Amino acid sequence: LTNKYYCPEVFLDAVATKLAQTAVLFLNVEMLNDFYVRFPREVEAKLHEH
Amino acid sequence: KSSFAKHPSARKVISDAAATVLADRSYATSDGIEISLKPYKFDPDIQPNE
Amino acid sequence: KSSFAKHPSARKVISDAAATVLADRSYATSDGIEISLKPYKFDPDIQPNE
């Protein structure tokens, strides 16, 4: 890992995988559970009203 | 693939329900993810396993 | 230890300054720390080694 400036490829890909997982954690919580819970209700209510 | 292949109005009702849920929740997820990423923007320190 | 051992007034001004800056960032720090804690608020999954 010591030649970070000599291996831009490996390093940039490391930063990409990290930012991916930590942003993903939030993502699943904030957004995915939000779907699984708001979707069926919204589906039923708009179907019924429609 | 569901039984709503026909009935395109009901189908459009279900699709638009999904879309309106995701589009209502879109902001908080984005901005939330940037704020949780604030520490990793300053020092994305890389471990030898990473 | 500093050169302001004498001069109790200027020392208290230096301290109080420090006090107000920290108090100025305290709220932002707290709210941001909450938001980063939102995925753990729902499901703080515990691995075995933890």
Image (cartoon, coloured by chain):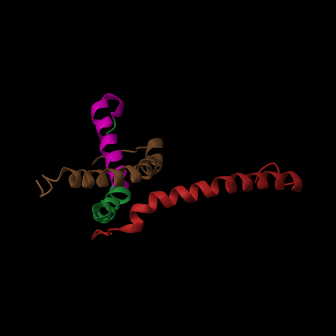
Chain colours: A green, B brown, C red
Residue A13 magenta-highlighted: yes
> What range is drawn magenta here?
A3-27
Horizontal side of C13 relative to C26 (left or right) equals right
Along the line of sight, the residue nearer the viewer: C33 or A49: A49
Question: In terms of image quadrants, where is residue A7?
Answer: top left
Q: Position of residue C10 (x, y in %)?
A: 86, 51
Say how many tags the image has: 0
Residue B42 magenta-highlighted: no
Horizontal side of A6 relative to C29 (left or right) equals left
Along the line of sight, the residue nearer the viewer: B21 or B41: B21
Looking at the image, which residue sits at the far top?
A: A6
The residue drawn where x is 32% and y is 28% is: A6
Examine the residues drawn in magenta and state their main secondary structure. helix
Q: Position of residue B46 (x, y in %)?
A: 35, 44
Q: Position of residue A34 (x, y in %)?
A: 35, 60
The residue drawn where x is 16% and y is 53% is: B7
The residue drawn where x is 29% and y is 38% is: A13
Looking at the image, which residue sits at the far front?
A: A50
Question: In terms of image quadrants, where is residue A11?
Answer: top left
Q: Position of residue C45 (x, y in %)?
A: 32, 68
The residue drawn where x is 27% and y is 71% is: C48
The answer to whether residue C14 is above or below residue A37 is above
